[PDB]
Amino acid sequence: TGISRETSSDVALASHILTALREKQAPELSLSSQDLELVTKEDPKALAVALNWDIKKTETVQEACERELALRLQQTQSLHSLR
């Protein structure tokens, strides 16, 4: 195939995932639990190689992507008022 398909069985990270990673893959809200998870286990060492950029730069995107995952999830947080 050469490309990744919709939510399918264990998909060995196709180039389609590395292409956006190498450029603009959103590991914040654009992905799901397994995408951000598998990526979370795919530290800059490898993930960077796909996005061959400065590790500090590839990490920067990784730092935002994670902080986004928890922030976007906070939507279910309780009200701002206190009892």
Image (cartoon, helix red, strand yellow):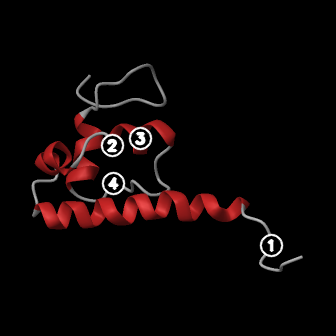
Q: Which residue is mark 4?
A: 25
* Residue behind mark 1: 79
Q: Give the position of the C terminus as an image quadrant.
A: bottom right
Q: Are marks 3 and 2 in contact (CB under 8 Å)?
A: yes
Is mark 4 in CB contact (under 8 Å) with mark 3? no
Task: Identify which amino acid the numbered label 1 is placed on.
Answer: Leu
**Numbered circle sitting on residue 37:** 3
Measured in 3D between alpha carbons, the distance from the residue under mark 4 to the one under mark 1, in whole angstroms, is 32 Å
Q: Which residue is mark 2?
A: 39
Does residue 80 appear left or right of residue 14 in this picture? Answer: right
Q: Position of residue 53 (x, y in %)?
A: 11, 60
Q: Amino acid at mark 2?
A: Val
| Residue at 64%, 62% in the rendered image | 74
Mark 4 or mark 2, which has the lower sequence index?
A: 4
Query: Counting other residues with Cα less than 10 Å from the Cα at mark 3, is it few (<14), some (14-19), or many (20 or more)?
Result: few
The answer to which of marks 2 and 1 sits earlier in the sequence is 2
